[PDB]
Image (spheres, coloured by chain):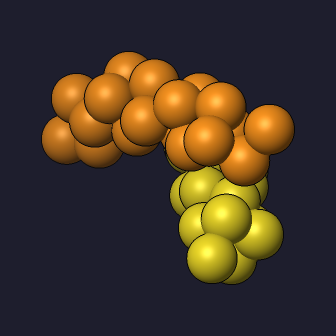
Chain colours: A orange, B yellow
Amino acid sequence: QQLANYDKDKLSLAQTKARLL
Amino acid sequence: QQLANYDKDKLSLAQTKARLL
């Protein structure tokens, strides 16, 4: 019900941190 | 449980969005 996007959101957050660096 | 990690991920995503902008 809520764990489907748990992976895609985490990955996208990782690449956003990449642009931040 | 994992929902707390989800909430932390959402907060960090918002913070990264603000910092990136």
Q: Is A5 situated left or right of A21 in this image?
A: left
Q: Is B18 situated left or right of A1 in this image?
A: right
Identify which residue is drawn at 22% across, 29% down: A4
Toward which corner of the image does residue A1 lie, by quadrant? top left
Locate residue A16, reporting x and y percent.
56, 43
Q: Is B5 situated left or right of B2 in this image?
A: right
Locate residue B5, reporting x and y percent.
67, 38
Identify the image quadrant of the C terminus of chain B.
Answer: bottom right
- Residue B17 higher or lower than B10, as above or below: below
Locate residue B18, reporting x and y percent.
68, 77
Identify which residue is drawn at 62% across, 41% down: A19
Q: Is residue B17 visible?
A: yes
- Residue A6 higher or lower than A7, as above or below: below
- Residue B9 higher or lower than A15, as above or below: below
Identify which residue is drawn at 65% across, 31% down: A18
Total marks shown come to: 0
| Residue closer to the observer: A1 or A12 | A12
Identify which residue is drawn at 53% across, 31% down: A15
Q: Is B10 situated left or right of B8 in this image?
A: left
Identify the image quadrant of the N terminus of chain B.
Answer: top right
Toward which corner of the image does residue B13 lie, by quadrant? bottom right
Locate residue A11, reporting x and y percent.
46, 25
Toward which corner of the image does residue A5 lie, by quadrant? top left
Q: Can residue A6 be seen in this view?
A: no
